[PDB]
Image 1 (cartoon, protein in one colour):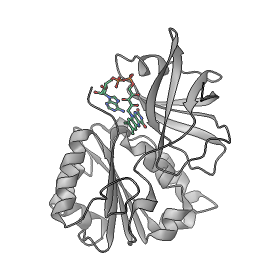
Image 2 (tube, rainbow, N blue to C red; image 1 turned 135 degrees about the vertical axis):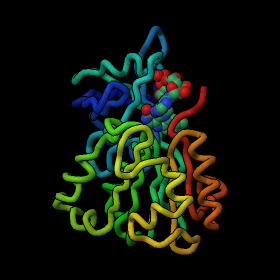
Image 3 (cartoon, rainbow, N blue to C red; image 1 turned 180 degrees about the horizontal axis):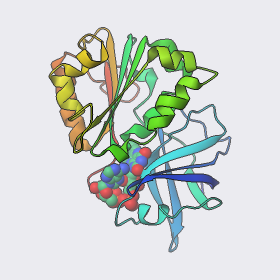
Image 4 (tube, rainbow, N blue to C red; image 1 turned 180 degrees about the vertical axis):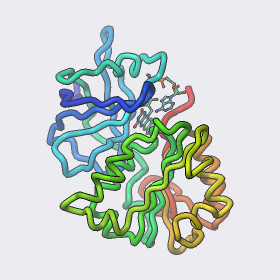
Length: 257
Ligand SMILES: Cc1cc2nc3c(=O)[nH]c(=O)nc-3n(C[C@H](O)[C@H](O)[C@H](O)COP(=O)(O)OP(=O)(O)OC[C@H]3O[C@@H](n4cnc5c(N)ncnc54)[C@H](O)[C@@H]3O)c2cc1C
């Protein structure tokens, strides 16, 4: 079995459909910030594995995962009961398309996400390299309800306080959460706010162009088609394949089964 066995260090529930947890990390597991790996539990003879983006920076000696809670699992129906000390299986080799290396040089990096698609971006915003490569980093997190804005305080209060890169955060990181169904100051779907050009007006940056702007997209399969349509409109060109650099990168946060 080519699977590492990690133990849960802590868990935290945001609401009844979201929760995060931290585990130990075997030093053989190396990854690029933004990549995903497979995690799972042993259930009735076979390990039940699922793809999960790593929500922690690669320089830390522990892992963190941001998870959804689906009525029927079979994984999250069980995973939601994770307790400190519980064991988890993690694969050996990470993979994925959301890495800064496949991004042609630019000055602004837009991270477009919805729901749990925020996960890979949590490791990216704590990567001193993205701050070294870009002038501004815009983290957009689209959601349905206010209680779904996980990591709010962390991004807003704690990150700017960092002793190692807090200055870069305050100076380069623009957090722009949008809520769809409830009263919120950034009302609507991120796709509509970007297409109309309002988003840029709100954040003080000029409209997107294929020379200064790069992006990464992680959300529902439908949100992706809609986001590509919006970015292609500004003239950006998607990377043709994993390993080939382009103006923007996309990856599904989950699949429609
Ligand atoms: C590259 C990649 C990265 C992924 N990263 C993550 C991640 O960081 N966190 C994560 O929770 N999941 C992630 N997923 C998908 C996720 O792993 C699976 O949906 C989940 O493990 C399925 O567990 P389950 O057995 O309970 O659900 P399923 O077998 O998926 O069945 C539940 C159903 O719920 C819906 N659903 C599933 N996952 C989600 C979700 N996250 N948000 C909203 N609706 C959903 C789908 O319609 C799905 O068929 C990723 C998938 C891929 C391909």
